Amino acid sequence: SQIRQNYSTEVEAAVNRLVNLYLRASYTYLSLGFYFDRDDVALEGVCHFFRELAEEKREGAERLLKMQNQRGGRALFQDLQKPSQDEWGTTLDAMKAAIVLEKSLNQALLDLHALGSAQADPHLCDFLESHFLDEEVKLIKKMGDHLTNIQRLVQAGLGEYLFERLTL
Amino acid sequence: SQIRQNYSTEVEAAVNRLVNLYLRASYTYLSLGFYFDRDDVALEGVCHFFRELAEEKREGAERLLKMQNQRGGRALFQDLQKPSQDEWGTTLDAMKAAIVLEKSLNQALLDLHALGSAQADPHLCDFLESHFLDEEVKLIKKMGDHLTNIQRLVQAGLGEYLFERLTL
Amino acid sequence: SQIRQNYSTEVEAAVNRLVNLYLRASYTYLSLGFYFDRDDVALEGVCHFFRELAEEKREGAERLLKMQNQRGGRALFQDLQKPSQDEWGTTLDAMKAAIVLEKSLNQALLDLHALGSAQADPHLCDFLESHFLDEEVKLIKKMGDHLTNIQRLVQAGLGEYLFERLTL
Amino acid sequence: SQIRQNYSTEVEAAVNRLVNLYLRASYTYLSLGFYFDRDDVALEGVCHFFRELAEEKREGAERLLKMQNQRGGRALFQDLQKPSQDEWGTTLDAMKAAIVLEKSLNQALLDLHALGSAQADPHLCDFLESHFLDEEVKLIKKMGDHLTNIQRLVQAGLGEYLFERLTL
Ligand SMILES: CCC[C@@H](C)C1(CC)C(=O)NC(=O)NC1=O
Ligand SMILES: CCC[C@@H](C)C1(CC)C(=O)NC(=O)NC1=O
């Protein structure tokens, strides 16, 4: 590539893997969202919370794809594995799965940052710090807050309704 | 009729029967609405929900009557049978009866559509599709959502109050 | 399902397959878009054209998912197969692949419509007609127009630049 | 210096060298710009593109000078070597020289960042990341895009005119 400079093949490959992780996270949130839209689940606040996250993850993937091209790397796409569940249980179950998902995305970001630092690639490191690392920390804090409130509310039916009505 | 074209006597008669069904549904919702306005029931959100449906059903009947005349059919009215109950029990009971009512209206629409298709009457089929079929599907989805939330809330008194306050 | 009415298992399954097709089409357009954003391809108008289609296909999938739930069907997601190519060649090559993709989506819509008609499911038939069938016809006409103009422009480098600058 | 803290003599000297590189880049772009303003070259879009870059590089030098003073380092200026060419050939030739220039500035930034990291100087590292590193990556991507389009357009006279008219 005419523009490629200080951009290792290792980082390029890792960025492609991170794109896959973000697209798969987006897919997972799409499924979560429409599950809460079921007539026999019917928690619109929860549906909206996850649909919004689906959009955020898709946007993250696209930001990574843009950066790949900016650096002269080449996007390679793989199959997107279907989400791990077809039915997501309670808001509590769903929020727990969401935090597990985000911690896995965060660890991937941290791993990529460590790789970038090993490869002496400050642009990559800065890119991750300004657009992904703090966003993950904030989102995980928020999910933790939600989990704590959901748990304190478990008359579980009553609690699940109130949380959706008054928090989401 | 000078204007009548491709409008079968079967469809004309069926449209008159559907008008009766819609007027009777409207009457049912009128009764539901004022029941929840009783000082010993006192659920204003529920009253409003049903009063609004009474207006929607009356409007549906009038749209059918307009179409009857547009096609050169002749409106024939029959007695409107009084609603099936004088007292409607809980919000849960009432919402269950409402969904039963709407499924019966929907089936009547589907039957009329099948008749129109058998009579090769595309105007009728289109009329039902654009003004009634999707509205029924949407309303039934909403009622199902409400039923699910009411059920999850059953401290039944507390649940009935919260649903009326926070959903309706 | 409490709300499900006149919604066959065949249609429910077919709607799930159509969701997969739309998500995969979206994925294909994502890849097409970022390919034209490569520094060694550099056709921004073409990139934007495909990115916009990626969004349209994702939106189509979500509309189908909403309808699935409205009817009381259950969303089931499968793996999303990666796009058929990693590199998309010329604008001409890409536009040809796009029209092949859209014709395949259109045929799937037509097949689902035929199924709905066989199952006497007028809501499904109307849903497809008002939100998908005409949109496909319009998009395919536009792609055909583009293909014709690209072909008339093939000094192929010059033609590809002018088309991107003056049409897209 | 009363304010100097964690600011190595090595970094101070390197920052002075980077100032020289940026001022020289600015000078190079000044020459490029006025070359395309010649009556026998006459490509106003190209002239403007380079004049704007001259201003950007001068602004970069001044930002570095400000930071030098903020940290308590002392600005030292050296002779500015004249640009490497008096006449810049085609837009293609000029854009190639511009990308060579920017890669050399980028490498200097990367070298300074590595030095800052070795000296454990996080303020320097952050300063470079937020104001220079991403700007270089973006500019180099843009130049690569331009080069690709210019090359696809080479009727070379025709191509050079069209690129200036429709891109710049
Ligand atoms: C918001 C959900 C994202 C979905 C639609 C998904 C992958 C499934 C995505 O993340 N990005 C796309 O460009 N297309 C898609 O289909
Ligand atoms: C925009 C061109 C910059 C020129 C004018 C140059 C060095 C030649 C500069 O970069 N900064 C200045 O302060 N003066 C100058 O003359």
Image: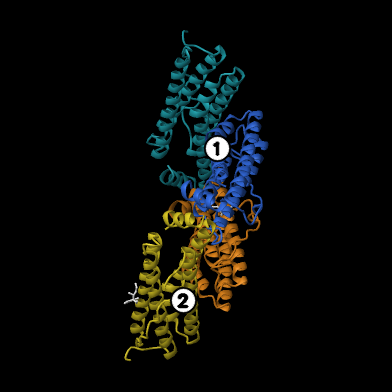
Chain colours: A orange, B cyan, C blue, D yellow
Task: Looking at this view, name the residue that lies furthest to the right.
Answer: C10
* Closer to us: A19 or C119: A19
Distance between mark 2 and mark 1 Cα atoms? 49 Å
Q: Let me know if residue B62 appears in the view.
A: yes
* Closer to us: C77 or B155: C77
Helix, strand or loop under label 1:
helix
Helix, strand or loop under label 2:
helix
Density class for disc 2 (Cα within 10 Å; few <14, some 14-19, many ≥20) is many
Residue drawn at point x = 48 percent, y = 12 percent: B73
On the same chain, marks 2 and 1? The answer is no
How far from the left and from the top, in percent, is residue C18? 63, 42
In the rendered structure, which amino acid carries the disc numbered 1?
Lys
Disc 2 or disc 1, which is closer to the eye? 2
Density class for disc 1 (Cα within 10 Å; few <14, some 14-19, many ≥20) is few
Residue drawn at point x = 56 percent, y = 21 percent: B112
Q: Vertically, is C147 above or below D53?
A: above
Chain of the residue displaying label 1: C
Which residue was labeled with disc 2?
D105
How far from the left and from the top, in percent, is residue B20? 49, 19
How far from the left and from the top, in percent, is residue C24? 62, 49
Q: Is mark 1 within 8 Å of ligand 1?
A: no
Q: Quadrant of the C terminus of chain B?
A: top left
In the rendered structure, which amino acid carries the disc numbered 2?
Leu
How far from the left and from the top, in percent, is residue D146? 49, 61
* Closer to us: C38 or B26: C38
Residue A134's label in the rendered image is none
Q: Quarter-wise, where is residue B119 in the image?
A: top right
Task: Looking at this view, name the residue that lies furthest to the top.
Answer: B1
Chain of the residue displaying label 2: D
Which residue was labeled with disc 1?
C141
Q: Vertically, is D80 above or below C12?
A: below
